[PDB]
Amino acid sequence: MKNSVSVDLPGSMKVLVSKSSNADGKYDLIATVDALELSGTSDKNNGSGVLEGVKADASKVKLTISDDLGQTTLEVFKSDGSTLVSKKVTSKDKSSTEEKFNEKGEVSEKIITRADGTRLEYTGIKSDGSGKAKEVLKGYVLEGTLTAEKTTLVVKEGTVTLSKNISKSGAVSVELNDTPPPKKTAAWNSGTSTLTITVNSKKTKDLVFTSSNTITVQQYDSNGTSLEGSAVEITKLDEIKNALK
Amino acid sequence: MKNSVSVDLPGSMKVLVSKSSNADGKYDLIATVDALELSGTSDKNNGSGVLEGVKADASKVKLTISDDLGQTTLEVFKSDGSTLVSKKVTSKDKSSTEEKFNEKGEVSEKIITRADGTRLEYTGIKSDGSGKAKEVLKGYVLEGTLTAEKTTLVVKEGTVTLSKNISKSGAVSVELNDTPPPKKTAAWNSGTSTLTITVNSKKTKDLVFTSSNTITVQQYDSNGTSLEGSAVEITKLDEIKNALK
């Protein structure tokens, strides 16, 4: 710090590495990270090495810098120092991986940043690999979910589901499902001159064709077993068409 | 006509039947029908009997009245009198059946009126029983077609076809078809990271998923075998949704 050299780092950080060595050959590293003074003695005079620090709430902070000034590995622990909370790995080339762990020392969440600026954001992860997913792309977002084998991001339009699957090892594969909406059916009763229309095991309408040469609609209650209202006579084509929706 | 009695008739007609009998016991009938004087001698003094006449173009007109004043059967022939053109039967109770015949002495067309005021209108009839159909109902019209067995009147709304079938002997029966529109399918090429979308054996779009983490649409020509345009990149969700329609 005193008369030393400023080194820029992956992820908008600096370190100050001492101009000269110490008693045991080391170089002094000081970095203000987040807002803590972090400190450490390193074999090398470039910026590489570990820096440690303690938050005012007694959480332990450990910043590792990779030998080639490539990779800053920012770990946060619980007060004991044994129990990992969070971990931001940044890479040389602008890409980062913000993790989070749970009570058990198991990964809860994961924000992946990509070199371009696009993101994979996993949350609510569970013991059996599964959880939410978001993909931040340039201009728009693909939501989805996670499993042990794969991420699946989905986009829907009416009867079409587009499904972008990203495998564990990076492999994209895409698929499409068009599935028709539930269709009307009907049954004719010759006895009563009544068409009863069934949608998805729910009766919906009675269309009745009278000896008086006219047509009457009545609606099934949303139970789909008893009629409701009273019988509405038809007065032009349009109404018959309406009943068929 | 001279000093006789006016009888009203089925189908807005009158006849004048003579007050007294003739030489051979008959009663004189005169009717102005359409605009012809029609004439005939009848056994009975009520209005019943036949009346004949000749149009100025030499077509022969034959009006029959049923004994009970029930039914007026207006036939028109060709000039020869043997070859039927048209035939309007009216009934007592306001119902009528306007036929038409063809060159061969076979029925071409048929307007059925019903007592209520509703109509069945068959046209363009053919040797194998078939032809157009219209049903004039109170407030609206059901179009359709004819066969030897049956009339079929159809009403459509999107994927639904309502079909009212009237059998030879009057029997109504109704049916419904909901049939889903042609659905998208797609094939993935791992080689090129391209989804190709097929609608009804016609390729429609290429969706391409780039190593650059972006999506590009290109359209198939309406042949459904070669691409067209050039590859349009995607810029928000909405566009991806659009491609799925």
Image (cartoon, coloured by chain):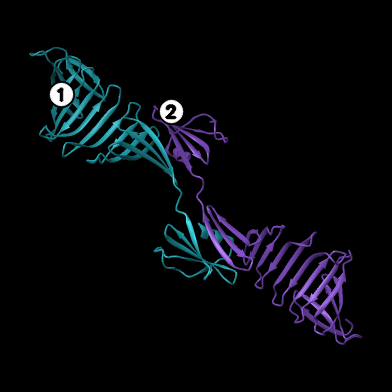
Chain colours: A cyan, B purple
User: Which chain is mark 2 on?
Assistant: B
Give the side of residue A193 with respect to residue A72, left or right.
right
Give the residue type that dot 1 points to: Leu
Q: Residue at x 75, y 76 (%)?
A: B71
Give the side of residue B194 with respect to residue A47, left or right.
right
Residue for badge 1: A51
The answer as to whether the residues below labels 2 and 1 share one chain is no
- Where residue B50 sits: x, y (%)? 83, 76
Q: Residue at x 13, y 21 (%)?
A: A40
Residue at the extreme bottom of the image, as rendered:
B20
Looking at the image, is mark 2 or mark 1 nearer the viewer? 2
Q: Residue at x 75, y 74 (%)?
A: B11
User: What secondary structure is marked by label 1?
Assistant: strand
Tell me: residue A11, above or below residue A241.
above
Residue for badge 2: B192
Question: Dot 1: within a 10 Å radius of its alpha carbon, few (fewer than 14), some, or many (20 or more) residues?
Answer: many
Q: Quadrant of residue A8?
A: top left
Tell me: residue B131, above or below residue B201.
below
Q: Quadrant of residue B21?
A: bottom right
